[PDB]
Amino acid sequence: IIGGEFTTIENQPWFAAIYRRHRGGSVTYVCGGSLISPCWVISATHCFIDYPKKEDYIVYLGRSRLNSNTQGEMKFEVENLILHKDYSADTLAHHNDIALLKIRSKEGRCAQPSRTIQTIALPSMYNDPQFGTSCEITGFGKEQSTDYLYPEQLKMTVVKLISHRECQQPHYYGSEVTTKMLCAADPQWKTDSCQGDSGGPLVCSLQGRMTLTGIVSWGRGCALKDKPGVYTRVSHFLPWIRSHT
Ligand SMILES: N=C(N)NC(=O)c1nc(-c2ccoc2)c(N2CCCCCC2)nc1N
Image 1 (spheres, rainbow, N blue to C red):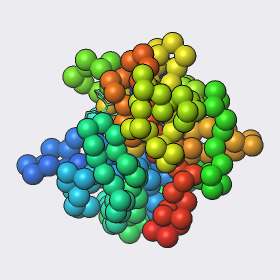
Image 2 (cartoon, rainbow, N blue to C red):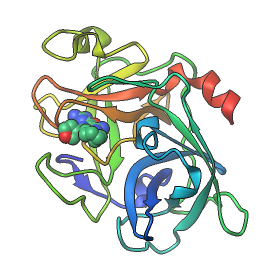
Image 3 (spheres, rainbow, N blue to C red):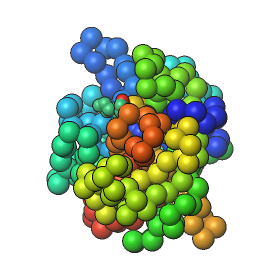
């Protein structure tokens, strides 16, 4: 997250921290995700496509820090890694960038909700907020494009939804953006998602309900003028989510 503010897991208790085990046994951070039910985390396919083996991954819930344990956290293995069959990557833009992780502890259990662990509601189909609506994004991704390290403490910020028409403009993204993607940015381009925020939540308040509107997917640079963050439009994937869960 470029700009914004540090936070803790109580302010985004559906946030899932996803790591990969290496040959040799070191564990590194991969991507964010969101808990949509006790046994299911939703994320982005591009996070996993290079290493598509479920046994390589570890999922934490209730975690506020990157490389230290948070009190009350839960650790899970990935019992099921489901990537979207129609995923594609061009140079920047990832199509159908959505993935499901079925989680299960070494004791064979799913998430027990707590003060630090809760689910996030999915939107109703094809129902998103209007352009200019302020939404929030959360993650352990880079604080500056030039940074080598990821922040040790969770961050979040606010961005505003951009219309498909505006994001479709050539000075923005041209036809790289489809109707299954959502664009969002700061009016000053001051704050944004970045590398390492992929897979994490874009949350909007719809009709009084906090709703998983987007999944962090891609962008050209981070917090660059005329280059918004691009998000998988969750309300266009409800059948795929339902069928696979
Ligand atoms: N909202 C944005 N403006 N940007 C992002 O959300 C975002 N940005 C980058 C990025 C762009 C230039 O440096 C890093 C990124 N990457 C990691 C993936 C592996 C190839 C490198 C790109 N993933 C992202 N999800």
